[PDB]
Amino acid sequence: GTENLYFQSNAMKDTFRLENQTIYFGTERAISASPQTIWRYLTETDKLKQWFPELEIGELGVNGFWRFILPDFEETMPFTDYAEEKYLGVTWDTGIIYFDLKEQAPHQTLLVFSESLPENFTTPRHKDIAGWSIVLNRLKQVVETPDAAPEKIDFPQIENHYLEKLTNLEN
Ligand SMILES: [Mg+2]
Ligand SMILES: [Mg+2]
Image 1 (cartoon, rainbow, N blue to C red):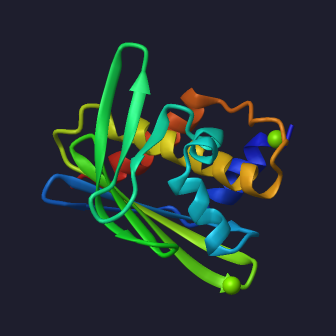
Image 2 (image 1 turned 30 degrees about the horizontal axis):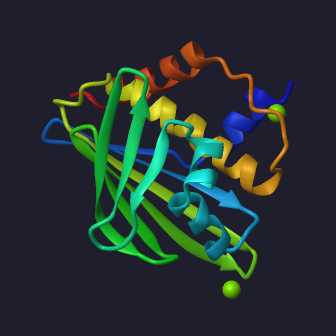
């Protein structure tokens, strides 16, 4: 299987910082499509669900929002920033996720993902980061190869990797 190598290849530019108990995480995905194509996967429910099945669009625009839906739980996630085909900031748990679509070439984009995880995050922070790394890998895969089989990943292994990254930030 190629799952381990695909995961490593997409973790290459993970970055972490700790400031005043808040963890900041950044990563990047090089995706062979235009920013306009990738923007649809953040702003249309049928595309958003291809990579993050629990999410749906609420509304778009400067007052837009996503919704997170599970059988036992629904929540709205207001946008904190919105620029068509450029960037999107969304409330996430007690912090923020941010998508920045950087054009590399007419059909190549660097999607720069960054996140703020305060100490009161409800999910253990390394598990939330592991989850984002996994679904961002799926986003790249569905944009480039729409019917590739999903990655059979080893969640505990990925979660441990991120545990060690965060633990290293402690003084
Ligand atoms: Mg163009
Ligand atoms: Mg695969």
